[PDB]
Length: 354
Ligand SMILES: [Cl-]
Ligand SMILES: [Mg+2]
Ligand code: NA
Image 1 (cartoon, rainbow, N blue to C red):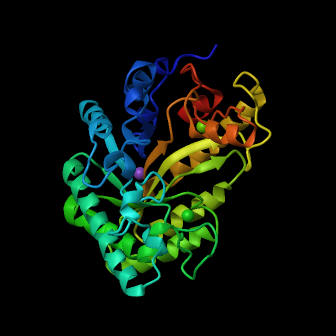
Image 2 (tube, protein in one colour):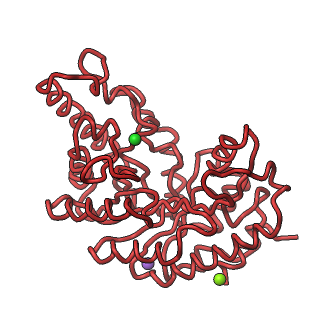
């Protein structure tokens, strides 16, 4: 029988000379077995949802801080670092941002002068959201996801920027405003990140590379690149991950791995195992080999990698299950972490603690 997580050596202790070991959390996960695992294994946390724009400012000028504050207070009490996720995203963002003075979607406006007025209004709203949040949390946050997922996976425009509402309304200016505002209110020492997934693979990797070089050349304050690392057992390759981190380090940017999970499935994730107990032990072994290689690499890159955060704690809670159910008629279970649903260690744990 595998031991419980609190009975084995701490991942944070294991990696103390290399990088933080973090987890994404909800306020309800700060106690019980999850809270115990958190305190034992991790020295950094991030909010899975509580610090997203819709979670903090759900209506204009109506700020709701309780969940985010609970996470901050836990980080303080437990001497953990804290990543802020996220100031800007095109999901989990309230629609009121993108409505004009008449209450209609800014994207539908056809008068270009009115479009420019809408751009200014949205950028003002964005400045206010960032100022208010940053002023509250600036003494607690150790890395800010200033913008999230602003780069496209394909090439819909020359710069490979995601054509979300932010882009449709403001072009790239929301990205500049976000970084400049975060710097202004968080201070000169605050570590400002651009976060994205599929940062290991092109064309996205190069769109992001070009975007950061463009920002930097314009004096936009950017300190680091967040690699979500929603990955699989076989993809992307170790050398793909390596090359991406080296590219960003070459620009003088920090790397963080921000949302790590190693799914048991390819894309699309079907067919999925219908329950956790249906998952064959061999698949956990393949995951363990993957995890060993990933953490060997992260250690190799530790002069340019400051923090490695998993997108959850243990296999009882993961957004990958929603994904599995979506592609398998409501039934399916993934298992992306080194701790199982009862907080026992998995084969992967043993291969990254050694
Ligand atoms: Cl989009
Ligand atoms: Mg190992
Ligand atoms: Na490091």
